[PDB]
Image 1: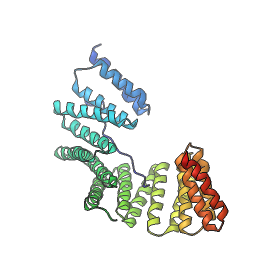
Image 2: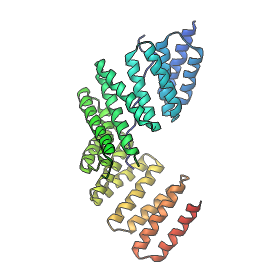
Image 3: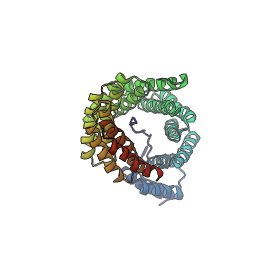
Image 4: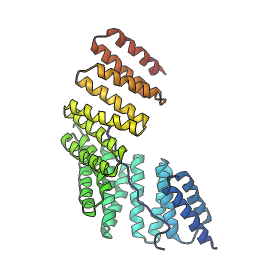
Length: 18
Length: 330
């Protein structure tokens, strides 16, 4: 089998905007 | 000393633990923070999203879906479009892994469209990679002789990955390029564009070296070898699998090493060398059983019996099948 690269995921943090 | 303040504190510990690579602990802190609660829906949105990703990394995809769904909804409630774009990308990625490609595509497309509206080029690029991934999984999930809609899904994937590469080149994002080159090469492989696959995995290999990413390096060599097989250049293929075998031991990765040995045995056979083949199949089964690997254990035997049955040793061949039938029945 071909080996795939990983998925990214989008991240959020509570430290955003303060 | 409000409820708001403790929720934040718990969440910070959650984020800290997850970054340290302890997602199981981080999940509980994020769950504690949900338990405590807060009136700030922005904070709550960020907690759901981090729960979704934490569960995704733990392979609890059904939970990941639930939390990304809450985050998407809440992002719409508060009119946070950036947050909506992110949640939809997350949802689409989870849907892709679950094998729900139609809704996966819709969600990942919403991430792209909103990133464009917001002129967010970083997000646009990620969405394009995500979209290539979904169309690739979609085309690959079916079943050179492909239905038209399957070839079309794989060719859309190529287009998304190439569009991604063009943006991340502009952004100077090398890790993003490594990811796209790898999956593009795999997509070309499935399409039977074997020369293009080599080119893509060569670029992926170069970036793996840049980062010192020995595992990515190992994937690349392995993908390169696979592609040379289907080009007929069996000699060059064995040379790439030899590179992976070397790397498998450096990493101390037992299973990967099993894979490397298995492949080389198969290549020599196409080269009509049966001794080398045998020595590698031997190592594979030895490492296989060593990993509680039943499927692998048997595979080596049918291989070995075919190889002895080619050597002229009609007894050790006729032997080999016997231990195979045993694992078969087991």
